[PDB]
Length: 304
Ligand SMILES: [Cl-]
Ligand SMILES: [Mg+2]
Ligand SMILES: [Mg+2]
Image (tube, rainbow, N blue to C red):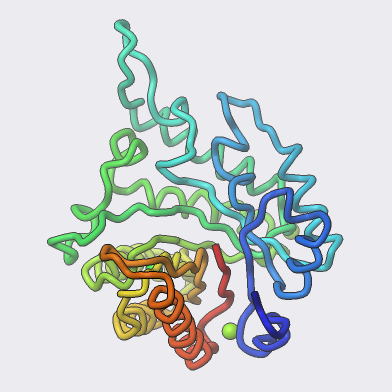
């Protein structure tokens, strides 16, 4: 419940977003969506399982209905998500062996599927989105050696098929689509959660800095990764000082930052309903005060 239209309050600071399903585009839900938000994210409709459920059967119909309705209603669209370990069909990066066990594909076949998916889906929606999450949730939680970002990457199905360079290869494939369609203004994001954990933030920073420093040196200073998304699945024991330290660390890469899936839930420990509501309201207030203070480098704040 918002007591003043949020997109109006924050119009000079950052886009205000919400994640939606098709139900949100009808009735009182659509009026609330429009009044408070400038930008939407599809909760599920643009994920790899929703867009390419089997090899070469691209299924864009429902996604196109959603994004055309969002634009007709005067809102923008953030694309979520080209490459993820969850909600991603097995055929992209595994096969069945002769005894019907699931095993990884080889690197070349898996790259080919990775590039084809990214490049087909990006070209289908074109500039109907303002941004894409190119890769989501690639980094382990609480990595013990964050100075070595490649050792800190989750051993997901893409990592097991392609190797530690697959995040870089995903962004190179998406950047080639934009190079070939120069009039599209679309920001390429890396998105992850638990970025208030300082080790995980250091690992993410080291990954983006390596990828972007090598790309910029070869491309007249142009960055590869334009944005870091902080998912913001926080709880009432999240320390807003740790959110500020990571926010500032990502700003120091020269990228924009967005908050992509913000929600505040109870902690580990048993809370009790009034104490829970006070904790949630106080964190939200502290986070928006921090975001306003850094608005020159925050493009969007989207709720879950
Ligand atoms: Cl986060
Ligand atoms: Mg801003
Ligand atoms: Mg063009």
